[PDB]
Image (cartoon, coloured by chain):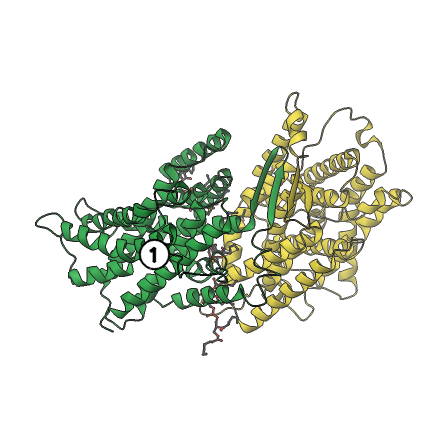
Chain colours: A green, B yellow
């Protein structure tokens, strides 16, 4: 609702300018990479501080996203076999065309082919903030469709990334991870009505698989999928937790995150995007693949029978929302960092540059085509 | 005021039987001596896990105690206009005689002289539960007097321990701690009704002085002091925080601490506390010094018009309330652990044995003299 994306923009530009002209030598290059090591007897964990920061922030953000999914799936839309045909078809369209277009001239080289899921990610706060500047010319249908599409897109991308092409972590880590989940199910079955116990068990589970990557992020979604929501005695823990967490994410979680990962050297940029395989695949994937991979499949779903277009919404609004949906920004940057770990910084820097250029271009094109 | 205390008793007996059992000491002893090292390339922190557990639990408990102190100082029993002379004089009495008796035998010996404040500490939850066991006709005045006396005694002992006979921290730690406090003062002065900001700044402060346990405990008290309480718009953050925190402290933190720090070994114990100087001094201070000192100084308080006895006391119940107040248990065990760190386990084991014996004897005597 409120235009809270200006804080994200100011944080991004502050991070971009901090890394140049006098700074970035004492800090921001020796910093954000100092190794940290935690040792308990034989057990030992070594990682960079940026990894810890990203893990914590994304764990919180995906806990919120899982809570939103649980609230939305049983109340409002997504409550029937036909009430969710349109967003599901839109997500299916957005999970095929941009990825297929990205891999057209990239899949030849494996080290860049591994990042096939970069353009499929979609941002949340930026698109809603962009919508916020329009005065009363924002139907509720557009907002509900946008969020219920981007959320499922991100969840599917994260699930697919976690399932395949993942390291085989220690069996002892999963031995205690397969018990906390069952403990969570037993606790929820008999009723708890206390978010503290659930949060404690979630912290235990998150620490269990902290040695891995995406699994730490997925722990938040798993935990948010289990907190009870059924209305009783005038109170509901899920709604209270959502209301409590909402201001923090838009002001402290998403900010201070774009301040860390975002920001490129921008010192030896030549040939614009270098016209290489990965920046071009990222730029074309989010600028053409998403607005075209969503509109066409939605049109197919808009056929006789199958899905029906929402009330107070025509194809033109669908196509502009599809244009806006081609924005990854922070989420796409995080996906790129996760997929390109233990890699020389040149690839990550080029991917971030391409993501920034594509997001800016898509946002300006979309805001240009809202009749004003 | 629920009964409680049974959880603490069962945790203590479980820890004792685990430690002294035939085939579980081999794991109980080794689990608490596992080193933990954290580093960021500099300022390495190496400590035993027991120290971390004690620091966290005591920080939370003392945050609650500081919140209670702030609540009761301006609108509670303490009130103003020096009308709360009785609890202050009682605390002054409890901070002199019990310490004097302890130091009588340990004056010459230098190594055991450090723990002069062992019997001054007073347990709150156990005494309150013992009182509530007979909660059929006991007046509220006795309960509030006991709680205020124990709280002020513990705070005075902890402050004196922190200020005097302490190590000196680094310049950077003190410099950081001198900015967070000023930040908290500015936040409170300018108005801030969100407890999340205060908790975050308190976490930063606690991490700043994490090197020394005493200052880590002091951080919680300071944070509880600085959180706003003034009534506005039919709500108060301090009261809500106290209500939220109350079930957790009496059900999770205290029993866990009791289970962690009550595992003494009953192997080769001869002549009770060997008729030594340290256990005998602890017993004399906790059993004889506390009630005699409390009663005597209360008598002098009444004598010279310094204070008037509260309603429904008649000085008959003051002796039994002092006997009940002569119970250290968890608090005295923690104080002994803090004072006797990096010392041979024999000394701390003997101190724990003496503390437990004195606490049990005082509790049974107090329950016997309450006329069943
Ligand atoms: C497990 C502990 C969680 C229970 C709980 O409520 O937390 C207590 C306690 C504090 O919670 P609380 O705010 O006092 O409880 C109020 C609940 O809303 C009150 O919720 P509740 O748990 O009392 O729910 C009513 C009751 C109803 O379910 C029944 O079993 C019905 C029959 C008995 C009810 C009375 C007859 O549910 C149960 O107790 C079922 C069993 C719980 C798990 C097994 O949890 C802790 O913080 C303990 C430390 C965490 C341990 C790990
Ligand atoms: C510093 C950030 C803390 C501010 C805050 O409330 O947290 C915002 C934000 C969420 O708090 P909130 O519930 O939206 O704030 C409203 C509060 O209920 C109530 O807090 P408030 O912001 O409405 O406070 C009353 C306000 C009202 O007093 C005024 O100064 C009036 C201002 C408008 C009047 C005309 C100009 O007083 C202030 O402006 C005090 C500013 C705080 C320090 C400067 O806190 C965070 O999570 C940010 C964390 C970042 C810090 C680390
Ligand atoms: C053992 C310790 C557990 C005791 C305890 O605090 O339990 C309360 C609480 C019981 O839940 P509740 O009764 O529904 O409390 C509602 C909120 O406290 C009511 O929330 P609120 O809006 O009144 O208070 C502001 C709250 C709301 O802000 C957040 O929750 C911040 C979320 C994380 C973003 C910042 C990074 O901020 C915080 O939680 C403080 C900042 C978090 C860490 C810095 O349990 C926990 O918080 C679980 C702690 C276990 C993890 C250790």
Tell which of A151 and A109 is nearer to you: A109
Q: Which residue is mark 1?
A: A283
- Left or right relative to A25: residue B274: right
- Left or right relative to A277: residue B103: right
Looking at the image, which residue is at 53% across and 62% down? Answer: B197
Quadrant of the drawing holding the C terminus of chain B:
top right
How many other residues sit within 10 Å of disc 1, few (<14), some (14-19) or many (≥20)?
many
The x, y position of residue B7, in whole percent, is 56, 38
Looking at the image, which residue is at 34% across and 56% down? Answer: A283
The x, y position of residue B180, in whole percent, is 62, 63
Tell which of B140 and A156 is nearer to you: A156
Question: Looking at the rendering, which quadrant does residue B85 occupy?
Answer: bottom right
Looking at the image, which residue is at 53% across and 56% down? Answer: B242
Q: Is residue A208 above or below residue A69?
A: above
Q: Is residue A79 above or below residue A320?
A: above
Question: Looking at the rendering, which quadrant does residue B67 occupy?
Answer: bottom right
Tell which of B110 and A106 is nearer to you: A106
């Amino acid at each position: 609702d409120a235009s809270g994306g200006i804080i994200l923009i100011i944080a991004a530009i502050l991070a971009m300018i901090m890394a140049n002209s006098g700074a970035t030598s004492g800090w921001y290059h020796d910093f954000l990479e100092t190794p940290v090591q935690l040792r308990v007897g034989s057990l030992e964990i070594n990682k960079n501080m940026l990894l810890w920061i990203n893990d914590a922030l994304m764990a919180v953000f995906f806990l919120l996203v899982g809570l939103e999914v649980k609230r939305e799936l049983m109340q409002g839309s997504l409550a029937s076999l036909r009430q969710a045909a349109f967003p599901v078809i839109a997500a299916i369209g957005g999970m095929i065309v941009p990825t297929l277009l990205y891999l057209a001239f990239n899949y030849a080289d494996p080290i860049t082919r591994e990042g096939w899921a970069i353009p499929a990610a979609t941002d949340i706060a930026f698109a809603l903030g962009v919508l916020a500047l329009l005065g009363s010319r924002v139907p509720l249908a557009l907002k509900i469709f946008l969020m219920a599409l981007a959320i499922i897109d991100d969840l599917g991308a994260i699930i697919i990334i976690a399932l395949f092409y993942t390291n085989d972590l220690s069996m002892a880590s999963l031995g205690v991870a397969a018990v906390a989940i069952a403990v969570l199910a037993v606790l929820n079955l008999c009723g708890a009505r206390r978010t503290g116990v659930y949060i404690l068990v979630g912290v235990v589970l998150w620490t269990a698989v902290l040695k891995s990557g995406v699994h730490a992020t997925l722990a938040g979604v798993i935990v948010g999928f289990f907190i009870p929501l059924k209305e009783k005695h005038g109170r509901s823990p899920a709604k209270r937790l959502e209301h409590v967490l909402h201001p923090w994410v838009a002001y402290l979680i998403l900010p201070l995150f774009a301040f860390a990962n975002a920001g490129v050297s921008l010192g030896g940029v030549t040939l614009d995007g270098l016209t290489s395989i990965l920046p071009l695949g990222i730029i074309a994937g989010m600028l053409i693949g998403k607005p075209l991979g969503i509109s066409l499949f939605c049109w197919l779903a808009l056929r006789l029978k199958l899905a029906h277009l929402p009330e107070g919404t025509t194809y033109q609004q669908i196509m502009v929302v599809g244009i806006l949906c081609g924005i990854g920004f922070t989420m796409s940057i995080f996906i790129a960092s996760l997929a390109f770990g233990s890699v020389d910084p040149e690839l990550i820097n080029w991917a971030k540059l391409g993501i920034l250029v594509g997001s800016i271009s898509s946002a300006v094109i979309g805001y240009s085509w809202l009749r004003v």
